[PDB]
Image (cartoon, grey):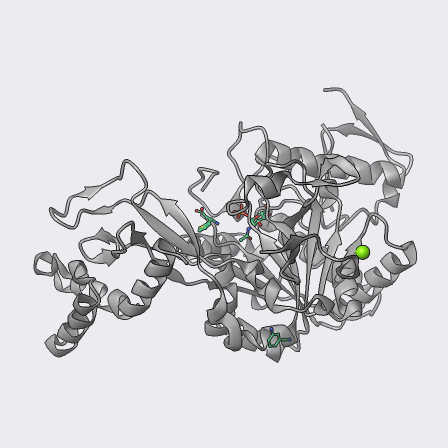
């Protein structure tokens, strides 16, 4: 507001080679001026230059994880599965388990609304959010069955600038899907400015810098400034499940996963499924320089993606596909301030509509004109010793069905999503003794009826005409 303050900021940016952001301040109303001022005050231009330099002029041994760090639901001792399930449910019952939902993604889907609101066309027309909340509701009920006391899994929902407000409205319109409003917290990750190919801050309007969400790796710094970590501490949380909004099969706060990690006493555990083929758009979990790590599908070499296991020439050497289902101890979140700044910035070339520095005409670029920076949630893995890390294989058909693409794509889209949920529901019923007569597919089982296939005895011997919906 004061010329003294506005000039000092203009000197900082102009000294930093970013003076062009003041190019149009004389055309500006006093409100558009204070907006430009406060947004520019929130960035350190010299820090921006450092980020841009490392992204635009940037300056190792890879093996599978050692078996001491891996497990698999597909061949664990059934006694371990039962023990891990029970211990997981006891942790839920003790009110020590929190969930962080990563829902700050806008693009491959072409929907205006947050991805969590999407109706994949199930007979219930439930959104991804609602299905996920109902797994929470159901899990809290199952855990009460082994304590006779209320169980609470707080739901921390991480949004972005783009998705925050519509997410909150959506939850409020659905009355938080029957959870207690005081146990669901919506918070927001931060942003970084978008950077041109020449290292210049890009301007979205004559008074606003173009910025973008700082990647799901922004979760950690967001846990601090939002107050979520403090809330977790107040609730006595000790175990956190973090996952991506787009997976309609996500086993929220999965008791087997939690029990497995807590009994191994790891700082961090993560779920994988067998990679479907060499080109699947998934990060690969592996051992890099003797540490647990993830190579993202956008950064891996073709030679690495196609390497083959020696005695199995038709199988991929690296096939532990990351399904974005992570466990943390609370102790680990208590260290965020020591290492949140060590997280790398990954770089994507983007077409960012902006104002031309010269004339000032808002234009959509032909070719990629700049970059976006993103920290990745899993880049904490190499901070974690192998002995404090666990990677457990799950079943894709039960645990991983991501919504990445629009209806009509043919993979990882609303139709494969719906088909996976309903194939799962039929499978559950059949194992419980039900019969599904199909004349044309599958059955949608509400999470409030069954979290993971239990509680379906009441359908033994009963015939079900697919498509069907089983609800309370
Ligand atoms: C930073 C991050 O979480 N990347 C994840 C995430 O990729 P996306 O770019 O967001 O589609 O989801 C994939 C699973 O669907 C996972 O394999 C990958 O490693
Ligand atoms: N997760 C992706 C998102 C995108 O490509 O838009 C990124 C990789 C590297 C920087 S951003
Ligand atoms: N738990 C824990 C912890 C504390 C400090 C640093 C790292 N890498 C982990
Ligand atoms: Mg193993």
Horizontal side of residue 295 vs 385, given as left or right: left
Residue 313 against residue 9 in the figure, above or below: above
Is residue 180 or residue 395 the one in the foreground? Answer: 395
Name which residue lies at 7% across and 60% down: 26
Name which residue lies at 91% across and 34% down: 461
Name which residue lies at 87% across and 39% down: 431
Residue 399 against residue 66 in the figure, above or below: above
Using the rendered image of the protein, determine whether residue 402 is visible from the camera's viewpoint.
Answer: no
Q: How far across and how far down the image is residue 281, in percent?
A: 57, 41
Q: How far across and how far down the image is residue 141, in percent?
A: 76, 60
Is residue 159 or residue 467 the one in the foreground? Answer: 159
Horizontal side of residue 237 vs 39, given as left or right: right
Horizontal side of residue 176 vs 15, given as left or right: right
Q: Can you tell me which quadrant of the image ligand 4 is in?
A: bottom right
- The quarter in which the N terminus is drawn is bottom left
Residue 286 image-quadrant placement: bottom right
Is residue 106 or residue 119 the one in the foreground? Answer: 106
């Amino acid at each position: 507001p004061s010329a003294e303050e506005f000039q000092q900021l203009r000197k900082k940016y102009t000294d930093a080679g970013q003076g062009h952001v003041f190019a149009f301040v004389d055309e500006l109303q006093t409100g558009e001026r204070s907006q430009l001022f406060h947004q520019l005050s929130s960035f350190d231009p010299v820090r921006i230059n450092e980020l841009a330099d490392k992204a635009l002029n940037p300056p190792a041994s890879l093996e599978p994880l050692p078996d001491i760090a891996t497990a698999s639901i597909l061949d664990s001792d059934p006694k371990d599965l039962e023990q891990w399930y029970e211990e997981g449910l006891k942790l839920v019952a003790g009110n020590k388990v929190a969930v962080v939902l990563m829902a700050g993604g806008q693009t491959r889907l072409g929907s205006s609304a947050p991805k969590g609101c999407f109706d994949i066309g199930l007979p219930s027309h439930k959104s991804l959010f609602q299905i996920q909340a109902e797994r929470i509701a159901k899990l809290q009920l199952l855990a009460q069955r082994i304590s006779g006391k209320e169980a609470v899994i707080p739901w921390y929902v991480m949004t972005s600038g783009p998705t925050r407000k519509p997410t909150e409205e959506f939850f409020e319109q659905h009355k938080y899907f029957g959870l207690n409003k005081s146990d669901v917290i919506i918070f927001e990750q931060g942003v970084l400015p978008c950077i041109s190919n020449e290292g210049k801050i890009l301007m979205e309007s004559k008074f606003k810098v173009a910025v973008a969400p700082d990647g799901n790796g922004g979760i950690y710094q967001a846990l601090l400034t939002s107050g979520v970590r403090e809330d977790m501490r107040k609730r006595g949380i000790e175990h956190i499940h973090t996952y991506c909004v787009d997976n309609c099969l996500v086993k929220v706060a999965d008791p087997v996963f939690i029990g497995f990690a807590a009994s191994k006493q790891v700082d961090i555990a993560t779920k994988v499924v067998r990679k479907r083929n060499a080109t699947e758009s998934v990060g690969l979990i592996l051992q890099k320089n003797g540490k647990p790590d993830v190579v993202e599908y956008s950064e891996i070499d073709k030679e690495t993606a196609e390497a083959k296991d020696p005695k199995q020439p038709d199988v991929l050497k690296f096939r532990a596909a990351n399904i974005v289902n992570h466990y943390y101890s609370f102790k680990f979140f208590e260290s965020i301030e020591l290492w949140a700044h060590k997280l790398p910035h990954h770089v994507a070339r983007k077409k960012i509509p902006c104002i031309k520095e010269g004339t000032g005409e808002f234009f959509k670029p032909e070719k990629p004109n700049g970059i976006k920076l993103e920290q990745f949630v899993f880049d904490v893995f190499p901070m974690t010793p192998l002995e404090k890390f666990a990677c457990i294989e799950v079943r894709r058909e039960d645990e991983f069905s991501p919504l990445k693409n629009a209806r009509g794509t043919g993979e990882d889209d609303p139709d494969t999503s719906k088909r996976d949920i309903m194939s799962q529901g039929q499978r559950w019923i059949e194992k419980a003794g039900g019969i599904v007569i199909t004349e044309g597919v599958g059955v949608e089982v509400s999470p409030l009826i069954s979290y993971g296939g239990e509680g379906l005895e009441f359908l033994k011997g009963r015939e079900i005409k697919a498509p069907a919906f089983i609800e309370k």
